[PDB]
Image: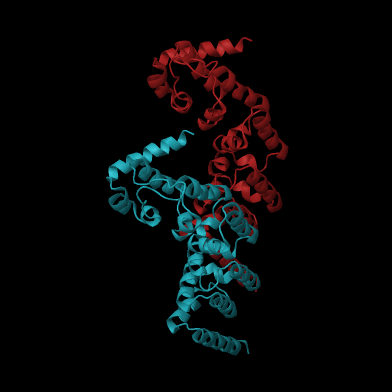
Chain colours: A cyan, B red
Amino acid sequence: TPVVQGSLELERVMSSLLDMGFSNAHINELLSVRRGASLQQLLDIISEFILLGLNPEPVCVVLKKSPQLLKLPIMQMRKRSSYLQKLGLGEGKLKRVLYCCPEIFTMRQQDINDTVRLLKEKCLFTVQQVTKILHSCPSVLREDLGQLEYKFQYAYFRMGIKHPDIVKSEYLQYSLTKIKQRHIYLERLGRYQTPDKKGQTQIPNPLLKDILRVSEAEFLARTACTSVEEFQVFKKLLAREEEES
Amino acid sequence: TPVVQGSLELERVMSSLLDMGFSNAHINELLSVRRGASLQQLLDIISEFILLGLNPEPVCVVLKKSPQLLKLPIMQMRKRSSYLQKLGLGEGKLKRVLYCCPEIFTMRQQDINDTVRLLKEKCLFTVQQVTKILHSCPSVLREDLGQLEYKFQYAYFRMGIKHPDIVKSEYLQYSLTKIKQRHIYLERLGRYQTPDKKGQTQIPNPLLKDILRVSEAEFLARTACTSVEEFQVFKKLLAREEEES
């Protein structure tokens, strides 16, 4: 009968998730989350994420935050899971990507190809670096190709940052405004020298993470060493400088 | 049964809209405003507006103000959605375009092109400037090609304004009457000098926004520095000067 089939599938599906490493608390979480999706559809999607190197705990995070991932037609989801694997986002590297950019399974693959193409041939990033860029700065997939090129150029030419330190610092996730604000302030304060020609400065510049990753309060207390009120005025002055060509 | 399938179909579109970003009573606003259109037509029209870079809140505003947008065919809407994306209007900056000019979709394809062609080849605006003109001044599509050319000529030749300052000040949104009224008053008062030949004046002229964007009261108090009664007479004198020849 149909009622008995559904109970045997639920048992098969519960048993498969227990074997995959899911807790009983997580299995109920996942069963409550599925907005009318099949039990097999819930399982086929979890299996793809497990095949992508994700553990059972992060799988519950991505699916609770983004339940629309269960609505994905599975065969197209597998085809995208394969595209992302050869792109280097396997071995659980897609954990950070799904949290910020869950659209990656819905996106057009030529739009993803355009972003990797811009980074590899126009910004001269190696394949290993492009994979790390996508892993740590998923926002670059949503970024315009022009804006993203200018943002890269600012680090390489204006700031004098070599390709590895751009990737390691996760520079491309931040806004050009935040980047310009903090870099130009330090430059004019004398706390940031542009390295040239051998990539050397008189005094070593602060680390990219201590400039961008850190809070405005921490940036001003430890790196810039100025008052808060002074930087607020600087932001207004710089905004006007940009507005006027 | 048919009654149960309609309730399950309604639950799918309501779930899809909740996953997109819409929340609480903003999902119910989309279904109540509908004037006999299909259920898929509501999601097909809204899906193109989210793809154009609009957020869920202004999508409820543009469709409540202009419900006729749901009556548009999806295939003809996609054609114009693609035309506007290459024109630079899409990818987010289309909030104040449809709010002020809701007849843009129903308009003739060639009448939009004639207005774009006039700006690029006859007024010598760059593609980036033309895109900014249409975003801030959507009323230029409703205007006549002759009136719009003369309005541009007035700024470039009569007032001596270079192409960037015309675009930045949002000059083309105002009426030629308002423009002539305020420019000629200041010119005859001696508070506006025409720049030539190097684009320089003895004293710098007031800013285009302080002339046009500002209220009649503020224009007269800060820029023109005359009484209200005096400008009312000026408007009547100038109206008569225009009427003759």
Where in the figure is residue B117, as x and y percent of width and height?
A: 69, 33
Q: Which residue is drawn at 61% across and 69% down?
A: A86
Q: Can you say whether A229 is above or below B198 in the image?
A: below
- In the rendered image, the residue lying farthest to the front is A198
Evaluate whether residue B21 shows in this view: no
Q: Can you say whether B56 is above or below B84 in the image?
A: below
Say which of B210 and A112 sits in front.
Answer: A112
B147 relative to B213 in the view: left or right: right
Q: Residue at x 33, y 42 (%)?
A: A189
Q: Can you say whether B208 is above or below B201 in the image?
A: below
Evaluate whether residue B112 shows in this view: yes
Where in the figure is residue B97, as x and y percent of width and height?
A: 57, 40
- In the rendered image, the residue lying farthest to the right is B110
Where in the figure is residue B15, as x and y percent of width and height?
A: 54, 65
Where in the figure is residue B31, as x and y percent of width and height?
A: 56, 57
B130 relative to A154 in the view: left or right: right
Q: Residue at x 49, y 74 (%)?
A: A59
Say which of A122 and B211 sits in front.
Answer: A122
Specify the quadrant of the image occupied by residue B161: top right
Numbered marks: total: 0
Specify the quadrant of the image occupied by residue B175: top right
Q: Residue at x 55, y 64 (%)?
A: A128
The quadrant of the rendering that contains the N terminus of chain A is bottom right
